[PDB]
Amino acid sequence: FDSFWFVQQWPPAVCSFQKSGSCPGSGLRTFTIHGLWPQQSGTSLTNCPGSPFDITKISHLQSQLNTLWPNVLRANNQQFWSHEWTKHGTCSESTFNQAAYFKLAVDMRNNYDIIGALRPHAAGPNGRTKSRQAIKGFLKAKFGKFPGLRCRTDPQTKVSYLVQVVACFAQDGSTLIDCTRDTCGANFIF
Ligand SMILES: O=c1ccn([C@@H]2O[C@H](COP(=O)(O)O)[C@@H](O)[C@H]2O)c(=O)[nH]1
Ligand SMILES: O=c1cc[nH]c(=O)[nH]1
Image (cartoon, rainbow, N blue to C red; front, side, top):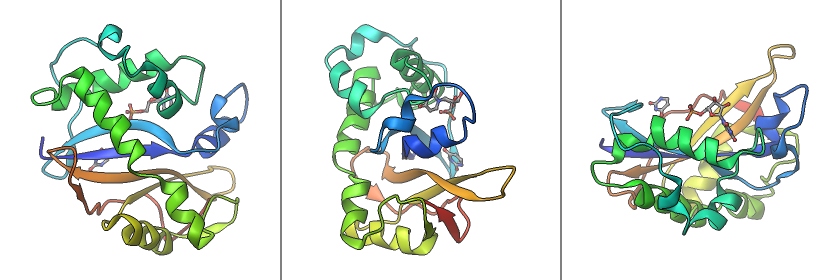
């Protein structure tokens, strides 16, 4: 892998697509970790042959992960961590063992406060229309690099909602780099 996509999700937005049933994200007004996705030549590396997920390897990060990486769709964090490790983490296992991978994600989350970066610009989530360019600009100014903005469209209304913010990192997992790929259009609800 040559870079990482540190993907954070806005729980309420992610859960806003679940039109029925419980969804913990609905009550979590803080960006949380969706996953840390290794990339290679402009593409996501997934399902690489690697070590099976081992929950004991991250007991030391468990409390932090419960807060920073909760499963926002259902009350089962481990299932989500295991899925993210197996589908993505294995792809950077050449240099980051499971413990180091989850630690990277935790550190990245603790060093990439999106709400804190948007607050000064009154660009926090309020269910109103936001500019992709403006949001990327605020984050570019705060962190020095452009984030990636990911949106999902409500099939019934055609309204686009910001669901994830990506912080791109070099293979060292510490050097923030500019993201260039967004799934969001020029405007979206946040
Ligand atoms: O809080 C979350 C966010 C996403 N997912 C799940 O993870 C997958 C999306 O992540 P990915 O496979 O593209 O890494 C989907 O199956 C989705 O339901 C969860 O279980 N919990
Ligand atoms: O991780 C991802 C997802 C989509 N497209 C990419 O280039 N990387």
